[PDB]
Length: 300
Ligand SMILES: CC(=O)N[C@@H]1[C@H](O[C@H]2[C@H](O)[C@@H](NC(C)=O)[C@H](O[C@H]3[C@H](O)[C@@H](NC(C)=O)[C@@H](O)O[C@@H]3CO)O[C@@H]2CO)O[C@H](CO)[C@@H](O[C@@H]2O[C@H](CO)[C@@H](O)[C@H](O)[C@H]2NC(C)=O)[C@@H]1O
Ligand SMILES: [Mg+2]
Image 1 (cartoon, protein in one colour):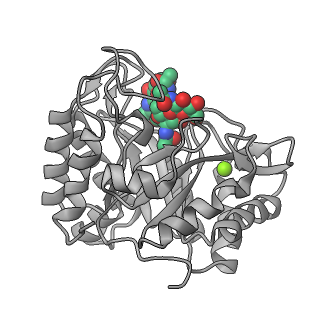
Image 2: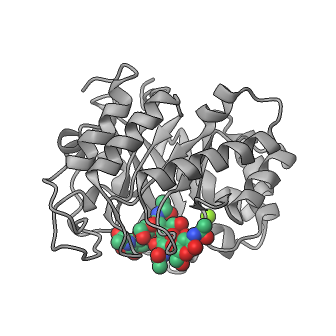
């Protein structure tokens, strides 16, 4: 379309922390990473603007022109809410109507076709669901992704309750994207990400028993944290390749990672938003993950 492009059936849309001073134009990231799809992080509640803003403080409309330039090369975005630090819109809103108004403002500002709710903190899932019922009614072309904490012993944690609530309320669930990272008791590697995927598969089958195996895998995305994780385990380039190959084999819906600006070598084991604390060359993880899309027709 004019001001929105198709996202492939099997896509890779890594997270960009939009608040960083190092922020490049999205078109430049497309050239460097090899993907022209990104998840833009994060919209939070800003007290200053009394509504949505990047990192809860940066004007909502700041990146509109970057998104239109990305669309000129056929790229497209997913807009993410939430993340590791609040306050979330869904926490601050007094009513589902107010919450829906805020989500819709973000949709309309970016002509968004896909929203991602990266819900790490405790929330009122009922209030979220009621807002999303309004959103999907008023903006029926917009897909909803839910990006949630996960663990290889359980799959989704409290996030499972969020999906259960969405399903029962009749809120569309286009993507369930466990964050396969930061378990603390066991390392963030390919083996554990695959265990998470299998657990989430079983979880979604319980919610949606009428869906085929392939329908369930299509709903699933996986998001590791590249290189050093907050718990000091390391998701290596070898882990990345193994996970990509598993993901291709299982024809899952998507991959992403945290994060684009971390795809640079850095001092060993140091946690930073600007590098990944491993020695792999610039953009190495990006190029491996792009292979997931390439298997299914993508070329850039
Ligand atoms: C898309 C997604 O929301 N992205 C981010 C996600 O946040 C992780 C937290 O950072 C992490 N906390 C630290 C202390 O480890 C958290 O770990 C918990 C697990 O969720 C949890 N497991 C589940 C099953 O309950 C539990 O067992 O323990 C751990 C520890 O409490 O995990 C979440 C993901 O679930 O990951 C990135 C990277 O950390 C995070 O990025 C940070 O984002 C903030 C803004 O929110 C930026 O200011 C930071 O710069 C950025 N850090 C990195 C180094 O760039 C996203 O928010
Ligand atoms: Mg929110």
